[PDB]
Amino acid sequence: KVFGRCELAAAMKRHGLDNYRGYSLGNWVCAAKFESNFNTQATNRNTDGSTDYGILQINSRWWCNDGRTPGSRNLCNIPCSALLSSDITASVNCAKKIVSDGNGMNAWVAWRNRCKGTDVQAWIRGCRL
Ligand SMILES: [Cl-]
Ligand SMILES: [Cl-]
Ligand SMILES: [Cl-]
Ligand SMILES: [Cl-]
Ligand code: NA
Ligand code: NA
Ligand code: NA
Ligand code: NA
Ligand code: NA
Ligand code: NA
Ligand code: NA
Ligand code: NA
């Protein structure tokens, strides 16, 4: 599923991401934008052999099981395929664990490089939330 901007903001809010660990909803939408362009089916292979899955490009090195990432963990206790669903629940629940891991949203390199310090509120501007 490719979400609309305000559509995703609404879903993220409904699943409790809005201000989760102090990160406003706009931070989350911005991260999703640059990670997956709002496409739940987005996958990308990493140089180390791990793969990133879903709207927030969650990495199989730590967070999910895909059966093909040697020496990895599955800290979210989910198959990486769950992160590709039209229903964002699994992505949100996993992202809450990731953002709690110590480095906050810096876990998402793209958030650091493209969202951090910017006017993230622009990402939810105009949305009925
Ligand atoms: Cl957009
Ligand atoms: Cl915001
Ligand atoms: Cl594996
Ligand atoms: Cl933080
Ligand atoms: Na699509
Ligand atoms: Na914070
Ligand atoms: Na993609
Ligand atoms: Na894909
Ligand atoms: Na992989
Ligand atoms: Na994801
Ligand atoms: Na997803
Ligand atoms: Na695994």
Image (spheres, grey):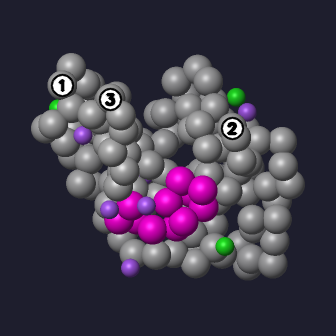
Marking on residue 70: 1
The answer to whether residue 37 is magenta is yes
Task: Let me know if residue 17 appears in the view.
Answer: yes
Q: How far apart are the alpha carbons under marks 2 and 1?
A: 27 Å
Q: Position of residue 96 (x, y in %)?
A: 51, 40
Q: Residue at x 75, y 65 (%)?
A: 123
Q: Residue at x 52, y 24 (%)?
A: 101
Question: Looking at the image, which is closer to me, 91 or 32?
Answer: 32
Pointer 2 residue:
112
The quarter of the picture where residue 64 lies is top left
Q: Position of residue 114 (x, y in %)?
A: 71, 47
Pointer 3 residue:
48
Q: Residue at x 61, y 44 (%)?
A: 110
Number of the front mark, 2 or 3:
3
Q: Classify 67 as above or below 19.
A: above
Task: Let me know if residue 89 appears in the view.
Answer: no
Amino acid carrying mark 2 in the image: Arg
